[PDB]
Image: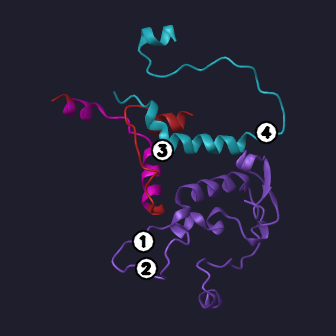
C-alpha cells in the first residue's frame, strides 16, 4: 500500500493468500460472476478522477465483488485456465487474461 | 427455471441489479429468491374485507 | 401458441428442438449467464399487466 501510494498507482495491490483447498466449490462459474461484476460496476475503481480526492460526506457503495478473493480465487489462479462461456470470443482463458 | 420464475416472472416484476452497494443488492436478491409466502386463509379473508 | 392464448397463459411455451451436438461449448457458464439475465431483466416477461 505504501509503495503504490508513493508511485501513484490508483489501484489496490494483489494480496498474499494461501491457495484455496479443494472442496466442492467450482471456480469456472465464479469467474463468470467476476466478469459480470466488472461489466456492471468496474467503473467504481476506474482511474477517472484527476485529483486523488474522495469527497467526505458522499456515501461509498461496497464493491468487494470486484476482488478475486470474494469469488474464492487467489493470485495462485492467475495462470490456471477456466471456462469463460464465450467471453472475448473464447471458450477457455487464463484468469490473468480475463 | 422454477426458482427464477417464482422470484422474477409471476405477479411481481422487480428491478434491483442496478444498485451499486453489494450488501443492499444481495438483501433484495435473497428475499426475492426466497419467494412470496403462501397466504393463509385468515390473510385471504382480511384482504377480501 | 393457440392453446396458451385460449387458456390465458401469459408466457411463451417451451419450443421443440433437437438436443445440441457435443462440440467444445460448456453449458455451466451459460446457465450462469441465464441466471444474470433473469435477475436483471426478468421483469420484461412478468405477469404485471
**Which quadrant: the N terminus of chain B?**
top right
Pair 4/3: label in front: 4
Is label 4 in a helix, a strand or a loop?
loop
The circle on residue C25 is 4
Q: Identify the element where label 2 is drawn.
A: loop
Q: Which mark is residue B33?
A: 3
Query: Looking at the image, which residue is at 70% across and 45% down?
Result: C29
Look at the image and say whether residue B41 sits in the magenta stretch: yes
- Chain under callout 2: A
Q: Is residue C8 above or below residue A78?
A: above
Tag shown at residue A79: none
Asked whether the beta carbons under mark 4 and mark 2 sit within 8 Å of each other, the answer is no
Residue A75 on image: x %, y %: 75, 72
Which chain's residue wears label 1? Answer: A
Q: In terms of depth relative to the viewer, which is nearer, A17 or C17? A: C17
The residue at the far right in this view is C23
Q: Which mark is residue A54?
A: 2
Colour used to depict chain A in the structure image: purple
Q: Magenta segment range?
A: B24-47
Query: x and y percent of residue C43 in the render?
Result: 43, 37
Give yes or no for contact between labels 1 and 2 (Cβ–Cβ under 8 Å). yes
Amino acid at each position: 500500500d505504501e509503495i503504490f501510494d508513493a508511485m501513484n498507482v490508483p489501484y489496490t495491490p494483489m494480496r498474499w493468500a494461501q491457495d484455496v483447498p479443494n472442496t466442492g466449490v467450482d471456480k469456472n462459474t465464479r469467474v463468470m460472476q467476476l466478469i459480470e461484476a466488472y461489466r456492471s460496476r468496474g467503473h467504481l475503481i476506474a482511474d477517472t478522477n484527476p485529483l486523488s480526492w474522495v469527497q467526505p460526506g458522499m456515501p461509498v457503495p461496497d464493491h468487494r465483488d470486484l476482488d478475486i478473493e470474494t469469488h474464492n480465487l487467489t493470485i495462485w489462479d492467475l495462470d490456471r485456465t477456466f471456462n469463460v462461456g464465450g467471453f472475448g470470443g473464447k471458450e477457455t482463458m487464463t484468469l490473468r487474461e480475463v | 427455471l422454477s426458482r427464477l420464475r417464482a422470484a422474477y416472472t409471476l405477479k411481481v416484476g422487480s428491478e434491483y441489479t442496478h444498485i451499486l452497494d453489494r450488501d443492499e443488492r444481495t438483501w433484495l436478491q435473497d428475499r426475492l429468491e426466497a419467494g412470496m409466502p403462501k397466504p393463509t386463509q385468515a390473510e385471504q379473508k382480511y384482504i377480501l374485507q
